[PDB]
Image: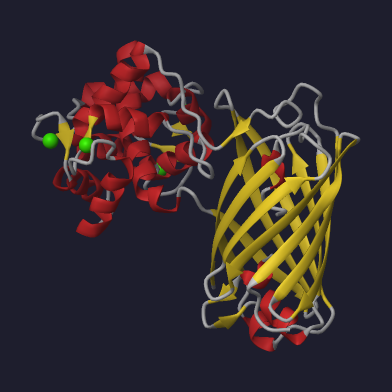
Length: 387
Ligand SMILES: [Ca+2]
Ligand SMILES: [Ca+2]
Ligand SMILES: [Ca+2]
Ligand SMILES: [Ca+2]
């Protein structure tokens, strides 16, 4: 075969014992990982969230940094590979997907058999209640706390955060973003386009559910900023350092009060679980949250440019096998999380070229978009592989 230009997919099987069957036409660019596919049901309206099909609906399109991926090499060779994927869901549901491909020049003919079982009859999969877009519902007190955090960034008090002000705060916390990085962070959340991050835009950014970044990740990263010496406790001096560097001036008395308020077990330091509880005496709790929200805002702004991108980690147990893993915390209509993990085993008919076995692990970042009716899916994928 040659490198791919066009592909087709027959994806079929059952979810909770209900049969589905879709047939699909697409294209992509093997030089950059791009794919697009149109799928239509042959068996009327889908009875489950098509979001669980998104990873399943063609790594022959994925290049590596300096040449072909092994997937591509196996297509060009003709000998090819087989794919076995399992997904485990937090409700105990499981899905298995097996693929076959055939190649005719630049054309891939793919078939994927999907069997999934154990989905709660009223959960988000069986009720089509998974979405790309949701936000937190904030109370007035939560909005008031975000406004305190916003004020740490708004150094001149003019009611908006500039690149100068965001850079100042990030630098105070040991991060050195470039001006272009600061402009990208702002433009990603700057709804009115003025070049600054105002309080409504700040609130909206903090309330957004990001596809591949959840509360646990943000609170874990925030703890890391406080816990400067990485010993798993925030001490009084570490708390003082974060507060001072953010611009929140505190007396020795106040630092002591904040530690005592958080320090449930009485050892004079704040462990990760005590921190989690603070981030979920009212004036001490509000001061912790002012700093915590500010730290989380920096983490969220820092990470926006890959917000739409999910990482897979690939290794080779031997010269004819790749094992890939990722995790996906789907978002529900009501802005809750629905966690899954995936494990995919690729079996190659011929041994992979030696340089693939040398360059382990590989990390592959994927962006996906799904537009769906009851009968039709429009899918796009963007991919990038890193050593
Ligand atoms: Ca300002
Ligand atoms: Ca703005
Ligand atoms: Ca520490
Ligand atoms: Ca403690």
